Image (cartoon, rainbow, N blue to C red):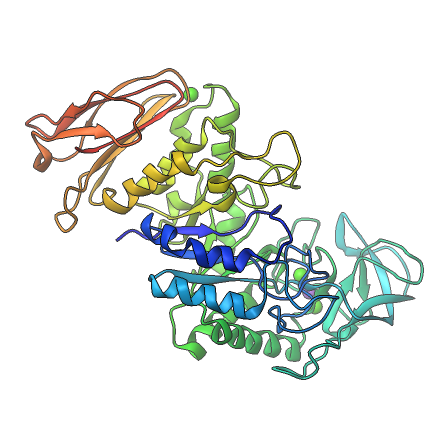
Length: 481
Ligand SMILES: [Ca+2]
Ligand SMILES: [Ca+2]
Ligand SMILES: [Ca+2]
Ligand code: NA
């Protein structure tokens, strides 16, 4: 059975504390549509109750302690999360927890620290002398105390910050005696520093503590894997070691996917090599190709979809997706795949044999931001494609990318899955037909479009070929009737 991931959150969901209960209630629906794993948003205390979760104040507070003015996180309380995870596990759905370990935000107090300013354009270049600043670097977890962990954070557990409280100044500051970590992205010279207080992975105590927390987190929630946040800003060898550590300690496989944000496949292959392919990465280049096709009114050359993507070179180390919380409307990396094209993009990642596909909560249920271009709920257009993946997308694949608009592929089916096999056709322009091979063992079968876009079926000829049709700017997925 094909595995399918679902990112179970959108950036603009309401701060109502009902999310874990919602996830629990969606268990049956997710299972029915073939979702085998869910990536849940950061489950620990952020800078405030409404923090989406990337503020990462206290990794040991999973909506359990009264801190930052709330007990629950934006999503609910720890018990509610535990009940939801129990429900998902009862239906064989795996759970991946978000891991935000690049920085810590919302420090309890400031500390006096000697620092220098570095050039935002080249962080290796110092542009000031040393001076005393007041940095938000003291974390004592006043509500948790020593429960689960007695480790407290001070400025010397970090490399720098972007705020001097004494002067209300926003610059990039490197603390005395610290050096940006390596290896990290080399954008801006060294991209170790992103926001808040940047964790110093050169510090032995910090590395040991983040590993220890990783195990505690996996055990406390009984997680099945992880989604790693902002990895281009975190020492690569540490991420490699952290993933190995958590797997050895838990004895579980712990599927892991990292979000390395780069348009460039080169930067992505370097990261995979440096972490010795021990985990996957989201296929960011593929997302930009989807956005490009959807916005060029038919002018995009669809043959390009086979190249320049992570999945095209590392089929087993790529998590493919259409849109996510970084790319949805109103976000800093906004590059939403237009609605008319969305189902075509979904057909591409859900019915092809390579890559671990991910469905976006915002695409299924809509996004709740306040622009005039929010994503509409498209679950009704995606459900049939999920059905195609769950029941028909098996066996040998044949690709037909011989046209600038109309491209398609087939799956012959596999004898272990009854009636499996399919023929998919997509076009970013005018419709048309394409003769495709689906396997001689399917000779004589009547196949029809499971999406409902075309009503006439296709009969497979004696040599295993069928002539499939697709309407303009549309997708058709034929399966045995
Ligand atoms: Ca960093
Ligand atoms: Ca450092
Ligand atoms: Ca085209
Ligand atoms: Na650092």
